[PDB]
Length: 385
Ligand SMILES: Nc1ncnc2c1nc(Cl)n2[C@@H]1O[C@H](CO)[C@@H](O)[C@H]1O
Image (cartoon, rainbow, N blue to C red; front, side):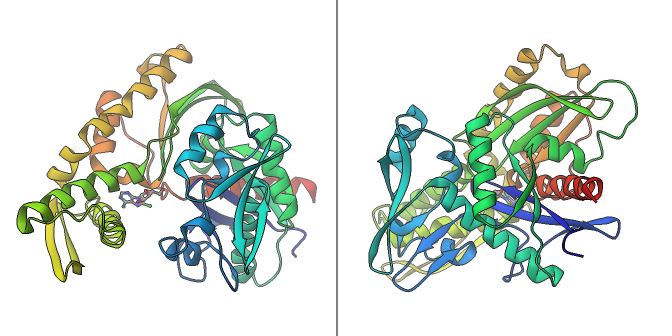
């Protein structure tokens, strides 16, 4: 029953996703708000602790006590230059407890501090409860994914987050490996298969090259930009609309925190529409000083606004190919991961770089990692019996 059941969890920097393999098919489980992905956010309020959508929905009102980006801290020392550099950009406090970072917040009127694994465990507990609500029984066996570049300390702290959350961690697998499993790229029989995973998420960009030799996975190269993602594209739309508001009304809105955040969420929504329509409309009632902001933008203008950013995704692709010592024609499969890979210009740039090649994109790119993890979790629990 429950002992023969296992889930696959994609524990992402900005969003997390949970899947289950049953009756010959993967089911990506929707949360209680009907969303197939859940924000990796934890909010501490005057009455409760919020996780996911509810935590992300109140981030503007409570920024000092809304934790996100815990994956950037997990398994790292406080003195690490990655931690010291990131801390300057977070509205929550990060403290040092014996060279280990802790996030310090106000919770039910009291000062509390949490290890990154305790924060990630709260996200994992939510994914576990989402699966239990869908299945009708508690599931405890899980496969949890991590970036291919995570070291042993980051992998161990992710497994610890799993244990704190009440999960039996069957295996910690690499995100590009879970994505290649999702597409059945390890079941093509004999001979070495070279796979390139292009992973463009909300806040990070990762390029991974894998070799699959008789079901055995080998990471040949990892490249990317840890500070490039979908949120940089939302911000480019924000700056455009701030300048358009200034041209139409001779008013600078940039300082009004509420106006900028309402514009940001509307920009993110319009950006998603631009992946399937050639235009998107913004409808913001009373944006600033009682002025409605009802406008539109073409996909052509959006592509111009992010042009340099989209083109920058090809430098880590080239860097990964040289590190792996492979030419373009030596890559057998191209896999898309991350919600931002739905952007048509991004797909066109990657397809043209690979000389007109077909892309593996039939599985929702923001779900492909949880999908593969769910497949692996089913194989692993069956072998355990
Ligand atoms: N349809 C879409 N067109 C463009 N960007 C998208 C789309 N869906 C998501 Cl999710 N994202 C973005 O992907 C990230 C999460 O993986 C977020 O930045 C989200 O906006």
